[PDB]
Image (tube, coloured by chain):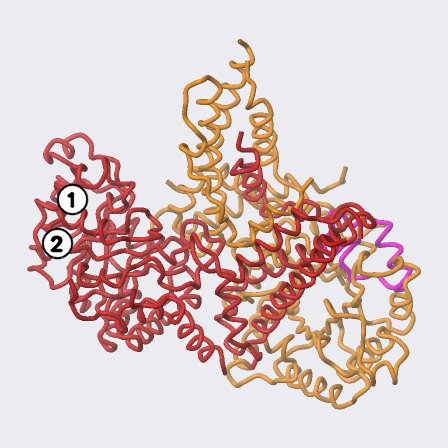
Chain colours: A orange, B red
Amino acid sequence: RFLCGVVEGFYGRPWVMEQRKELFRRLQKWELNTYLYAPKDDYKHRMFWREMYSVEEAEQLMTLISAAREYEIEFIYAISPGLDITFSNPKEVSTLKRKLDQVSQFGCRSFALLFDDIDHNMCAADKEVFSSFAHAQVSITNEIYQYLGEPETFLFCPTEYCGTFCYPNVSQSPYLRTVGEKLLPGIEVLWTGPKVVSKEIPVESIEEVSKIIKRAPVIWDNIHANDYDQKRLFLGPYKGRSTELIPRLKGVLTNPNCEFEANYVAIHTLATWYKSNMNGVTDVLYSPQMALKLALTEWLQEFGVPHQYSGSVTLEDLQLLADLFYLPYEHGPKGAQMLREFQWLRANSSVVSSEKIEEWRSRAAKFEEMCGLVMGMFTRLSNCANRTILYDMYSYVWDIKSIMSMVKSFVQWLGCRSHSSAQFLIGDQEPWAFRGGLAGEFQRLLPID
Amino acid sequence: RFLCGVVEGFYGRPWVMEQRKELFRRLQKWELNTYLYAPKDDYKHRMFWREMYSVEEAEQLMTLISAAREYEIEFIYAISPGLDITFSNPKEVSTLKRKLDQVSQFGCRSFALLFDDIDHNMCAADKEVFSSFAHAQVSITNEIYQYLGEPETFLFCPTEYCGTFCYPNVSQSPYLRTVGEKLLPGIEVLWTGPKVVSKEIPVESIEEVSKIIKRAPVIWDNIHANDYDQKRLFLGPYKGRSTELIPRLKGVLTNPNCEFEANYVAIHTLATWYKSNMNGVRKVLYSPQMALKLALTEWLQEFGVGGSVTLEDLQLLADLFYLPYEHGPKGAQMLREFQWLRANSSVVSSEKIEEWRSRAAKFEEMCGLVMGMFTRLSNCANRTILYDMYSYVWDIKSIMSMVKSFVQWLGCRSHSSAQFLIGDQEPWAFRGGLAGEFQRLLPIDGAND
């Protein structure tokens, strides 16, 4: 039993039920088998957890679970009470029991309770009754696990769910020691990696946290998570994770972008990565570039379902789009090539000599060709017939077009200003000082590398 | 008489029909009377305008027109033929006639021809039949206008509508002379301003346009439109417009933000500019500050069901996202305080450093006010208003917290190391993506020769 699926786990704009039914269709085509419902800004889930659903909310949740059971996807209703809860008071425990009982009647078999992004200080009665935070949380998890008759897949996310959040280490922390000692063995734990956003989840960190919890954890994976930076978007493949982590784990649950239609690659490459191996003890039987190419090919076929009726987008346009928006700690090959060409062009911009003028103007012409490629990419993407995918990522491609036009203008200005032929950079483009709207001003007034 | 209303005329995701009915309810509540439907990223309006409506969206447009007529708002179905239109081809004119005629059979009574961003001239036989491009546009506008038997309100938007678009000057341009002579009266024109964002439309620019168009223009407002960057919104007043423009104009149409729920303040302050100030003809009196206070009071009344949001939070929110050019008083105060502190940064922790610490204490207090504004706005009952503007308040929250940590490092500059915090966020994990990196590498005023 392996829990390979998608956790909705971001902040702000939760998905709609039609999007989740399309997600359940998408997982069943890709042989994935789980879905963890935990949207942080759904107000019946986090900010108010004592409040019960209405009749229409129960109906849409009931048909959501029915669509999941139709599509062989294990719906896991999670619930995060940790912002305001008295664990010592049994009234909050019984209210949580009532809420989990009402969601039991909607057809849910798998459940979870989540304790994330909360301060480590407790109440006065919680400090009076119980010794530490982890003892109270593991007593709540054991009480809910006994109250629901020990479900087959129950998930528990700790407050120190990554390597930076736990102190002093992953092994000397008293929190993970209490969690590993006092927990029932059928309850799977959640984990993220060395950070909240992990560049890599190495094998040895998984093995030492499997020592400290005495179980194989399920990695909540915020690789393509979009909630911390809403100016960014990630369309890279499922990289940074070795294929030998599958026998050392109980599940991989990816937390994708806040926009649903930008998540074809981020779930399909996870499906290809899970299809690499399933058992047995720079990567063997998995290439992230080949999984990225397969994801973009199937996504181009998704684009071609309405095609052009009611130029079209090509595969090279999608590859440029994925290379422009790749990873929280990486860019694409084309994006890094454009970065190093612009850094070269602004290096010797002030003094350019002969053969030096020849190579400068040739690489400036190559940069203008790449700028025309991104203009053609945006124009062919805006002429597509799948309108929902266009509306989900219109701000990002609009922002990269509106930046790259002025970058193309400044490279044309530098081509003018290599020789003494008057002009000004102000006369080429107006030097605006209001990008971001008092956020980019503070961002540019803050130091970078 | 006067066409004071809202043009839904941006790039991005167009609004759904139910929030358009909510918009019609708000326009009925604020004594506005117009709505210019022209969403530029719609696959039936701008591109593929020749395609007839389907058998499931025709009833949606019919119910939208009937909901407009219920609240006594003039639905103006604009159409943008200017992508691949052949003006001299009569079959294209017949397809345009059938397309407008099927909206005329949907109950729509006002129509508009829109010619934005088509300033490229005609070609082959199209360019030689007509003497100028404007002659072709006013001839097909007169043909459509007499085909419909002269409707009461018809709007012709040229491509030379911006003051910098008209070449040369305003009066010396041949386009505005051809439009002002060879177009029939009763077809009112659309004029944005001396700029495309229109910081200040004065009386004299309106006189210089009205002497060449021989009528009064209905003024387009991109004063709160965020379709050019989509990284900020605008909650400011209707600043930059004299009260005496109402007898010299035929209408004012406001293009608001692409997020619908952030448009309460801008449309309401337009309403307090019009219906509370000089409805009559009078050939300074409107206070933008009191209009902003009234708009924020009514928006606070919208915000109720209880997340305890106060009016100081909304004044702070409107000051954080204020105008395309200006900022709020509190936002400019925070920016000038932060640049004073980063200019007068203490080497170690007499007179200078004490005043520095006092201003740093006030700065961290108002940063905590920003945090309180976000955490009270996240607890509001009406979730859709939160979901529309979540990215902007999240961005300003995270940027304000990093700026507060940088001020905390600046208070102990000799003691602490690795700048603000070494937490693998020195590029803020490449904030903005490639758009942010190329924007920071653009020489606005830092590397400006």
- Considering only vertical position in the picture, is B352 above or below B1? above
Disc 2 chain ID: B
- Residue for point 44% across, 52% down: A390
| Residue bearing mark 1 | B137
Asked whether residue B50 appears in the rendered view, the answer is no
Location of residue A375 in the rendering, given as x and y in whole percent from the top left corner:
43, 37
- Asked if marks 1 and 2 fall on the same chain, the answer is yes
Location of residue B372 in the rendering, given as x and y in whole percent from the top left corner:
62, 70
Would residue A18 appear left or right of A154 to someone viewing this image?
left
Q: What amino acid type is highlighted by mark number 1?
A: Gln
- Residue for point 70% across, 57% down: B355
Q: What amino acid type is highlighted by mark number 2?
A: Arg
Q: Earlier in the sequence, mark 1 or mark 2?
A: 1
Q: From which residue to which does the magenta span run?
A: A191-217
Q: Name the quadrant containing residue B65.
A: bottom left
Q: Check the picture and name the quadrant holding the N terminus of chain B.
A: bottom left
Give SS at disc 1.
Answer: helix
Give SS at disc 2.
Answer: loop
Residues marked 1 and 2 touching at CB (< 8 Å): no
| Residue bearing mark 2 | B215
- Residue for point 48% across, 52% down: A395
Would residue A259 appear left or right of B254 to someone viewing this image?
right
Q: Nearer the viewer, residue B81 or B266?
A: B266
Crowding around mark 2 (Cα neighbors within 10 Å: few <14, some 14 to 19, many 20+) is some
Q: Nearer the viewer, residue A351 or A73?
A: A351
- Considering only vertical position in the picture, is A363 above or below B365? above
Q: CA distance from mark 1 to mark 2?
A: 18 Å
